Length: 38
Length: 202
Ligand SMILES: Nc1nc2c(ncn2[C@@H]2O[C@H](COP(=O)(O)OP(=O)(O)O)[C@@H](O)[C@H]2O)c(=O)[nH]1
Ligand SMILES: [Mg+2]
Ligand SMILES: [Zn+2]
Image 1 (cartoon, protein in one colour):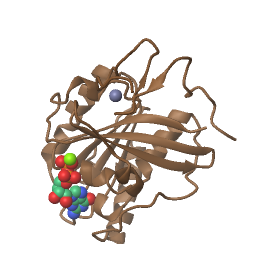
Image 2 (image 1 turned 90 degrees about the vertical axis):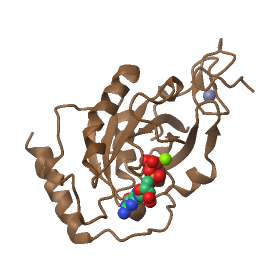
Image 3 (image 1 turned 135 degrees about the vertical axis):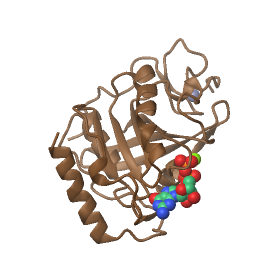
C-alpha cells in the first residue's frame, strides 16, 4: 500500500522554503516564519 | 507519495533536545536555520512499509523556558515531543507546563513524552515514578540520545497515530551518529519492564 492522500497538498497550497510549513494560496509570506514566498 | 509533518521538539534547556535530533545524520546535514524564529528545522525521513514519512523537527537555538518560544514556533504543529532529563527532576516538573503551553496553541495533536539521558546510572526520575494519564494522544519512552537508545520509538508511535495505521513499521533504521556512550542492557531491560507495569496499572 501507499499513503491515503488526506495528507496531500490541497489546491493552491505551497510549502515554505525556509521552514517547510504549508501555507494557503492567498498567503504571500509564511504564516509561521514570515519569510516571503520564493 | 511522501507525507511530511511538522514536529515541535520542546522541553527545558539542557535536557538533550539538540543532541537527540542531531542523531539523525541526514536530518542534520539537510537542516534549515529559520533566522526570524531562531529555530533549526531538521527534515527527518523514516522509511515505512507504506513509503517514506518526513518529520520536520523544530529545535530551538536557545534555552527558552515554557512560554518563551516565539508564536511562529507552534504554528501548524501536527505532533510534538516533550523532552526532559531523568537526572533533573525540575525538567520533569516542567513537563505539564510545556504540555499546557502546547495544547493552548495546537489543541489535540499527538504528543510523545521522552525522558532522556537514561544511560546515566544515577537516575533521579525513576521509571516507576513517571506519571501516566488516560490520554490516548500521549505516550512515554525512555531515551538516551548519546547511545541512540529507543531513538526511533517516538517517531514510530507518532507515525502510527498520524497515519492511523497501528501496524506501520520502519523497514530500515535511519543512519544515526555512532553511539558515544553505552546503554547498560540490564538497566534497559529493567526500565522497559518497569514502564510496562506503570503503563498497565493506570
Ligand atoms: N549521558 C548523556 N548526556 C546527554 C544526553 N543528551 C544530551 N546530553 C548532554 O546534555 C547537555 C545538553 O545537551 P543539549 O542537546 O544541548 O540540550 P538542549 O538544551 O535541550 O538542546 C549536553 O552536555 C549533552 O551532551 C544523553 O542522552 N546521555
Ligand atoms: Mg538545544
Ligand atoms: Zn516558513
